Amino acid sequence: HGGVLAYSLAGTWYNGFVPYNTPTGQSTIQREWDTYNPITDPTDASISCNINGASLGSAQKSATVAAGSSVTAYWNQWPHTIGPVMVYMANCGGDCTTATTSSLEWFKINQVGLVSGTLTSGTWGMGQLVANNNSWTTSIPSSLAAGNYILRHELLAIHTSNQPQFYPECAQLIVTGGEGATPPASYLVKLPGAYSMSDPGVNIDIYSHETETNYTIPGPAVWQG
Ligand SMILES: *[C@@H]1O[C@H](CO)[C@@H](O)[C@H](O)[C@H]1NC(C)=O
Ligand SMILES: *[C@@H]1O[C@H](CO)[C@@H](O)[C@H](O)[C@H]1NC(C)=O
Ligand SMILES: [Cu+2]
Ligand code: NA
Image 1 (cartoon, rainbow, N blue to C red):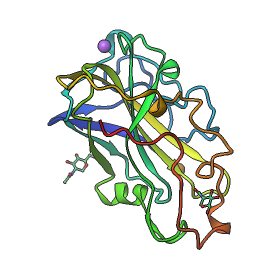
Image 2: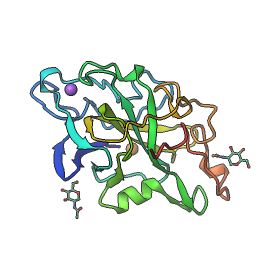
Image 3: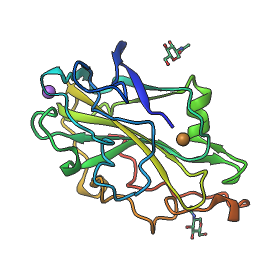
C-alpha cells in the first residue's frame, strides 16, 4: 500500500501527487492517483496511470531530461516484499497533459522479478526496492527518440493467493537529445491489454508453489534501446 511519492530525475527533485487530498491546488510532474490501494483487476481501465490518472491541466508539470539520464522513483516505507518491479514508458504522441494514457503504446525499459531462490523464500525486485531506501533507479534508454513521454513505475505485489495487486504511477517527461530510436511493434503493448488472469505471473498462488524458482514477469520484453 502506497505508491511513488516523489522523483529525482537527472539530478533534480520533483514532488509527486499527494493522494487523498483534492487535486485542486496540487502541481506536479506526476499524474493524479487518489489512494494507496492496489488495482486488483489486471484489465482495469485505469491500470495505466492509476485511479483517476487524471492530468492536472494548467497545474500539470513535465520533467525535461536527456535520453540516457538516470531517473529515480521514491516510495513510502513500502510494506510488501514479494513480486516484480517494472518501469514502462510511452510516447504521448503530442502533449502528455492532454493525452489519454490508456490509448498509448507502452514499452518496458526495466524490470526485476525473482532474482534468486523460490517464490516464497527468494529475493525479489520489490524486496530490493525496499532495501534501497524504498526507491528504484534506472536510466532512460540512451538511443530513445526525442519527444513527450509518460514514465510509468509499477509494483506487482503477489503475496495474496490469486489476487494480484498492481500499484502504478505515471510522470510526464520531455525527452531531449537521443538517437531517434523507437521500440519495434513487438515490444509495444496497451494498458489495459498487456495483462490478464491467464498470465502465470498475474494469477498466482505462491504458497502452493514454494519450491518454484521461475517467474515469468507479465507484460512485454524489456527494450534497452
Ligand atoms: C531516501 O529517500 C528519501 C525520499 O523518500 C530522500 O529524501 C533521501 O534523500 C533518500 N536518502 C538517500 C540516502 O538516498
Ligand atoms: C514456471 O515454469 C513452468 C514450466 O516449467 C510454467 O508452466 C509456469 O507458468 C512458470 N511459472 C511462472 C510464474 O512463470
Ligand atoms: Cu498493501
Ligand atoms: Na506538456
